[PDB]
Image 1 (spheres, rainbow, N blue to C red):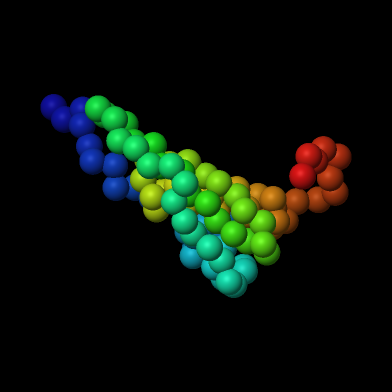
Image 2 (image 1 turned 45 degrees about the vertical axis):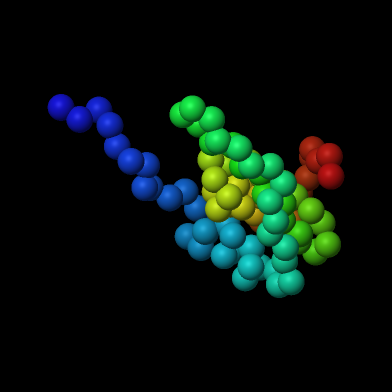
Length: 91
């Protein structure tokens, strides 16, 4: 029996474009830099920052590129949610 796999499956975003490449189509002149980076006994913890429309959003993932994905989604869900009227919103 197996009970073990190497996680190769890739999460994306609102569309099948991958949040990073998608955001780079939705907006141009973006910035992707590293904020936090560490690796423990069995788990990883990376945090990347993305600049969209001058606004900086930070996301955390198990590596740089996955952290970029969450950072991008952080901007996408805020700038391009495509949702109806807003009854609840902070920023």
